[PDB]
Length: 60
Image (cartoon, rainbow, N blue to C red; front, side, top):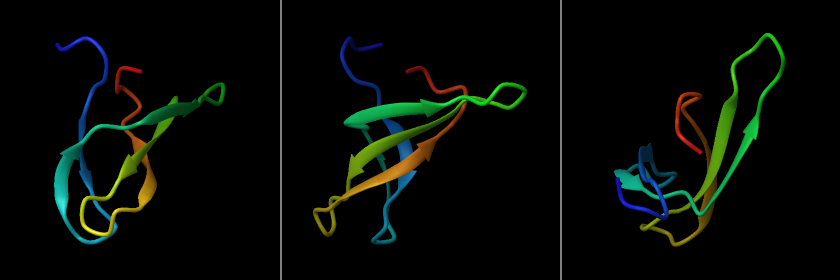
């Protein structure tokens, strides 16, 4: 894969579906649970930044 960033197929708040690359990624890993991740994306329709949970298996 390309060295640097990694994109995910994500729904936009505007109602689009595109593979956007998270600008900032963070995780919430509770013990006994799964390590959920959230990434901040930019919506290409409105222009705003939206955070969206990534898959727990998503490589961050």
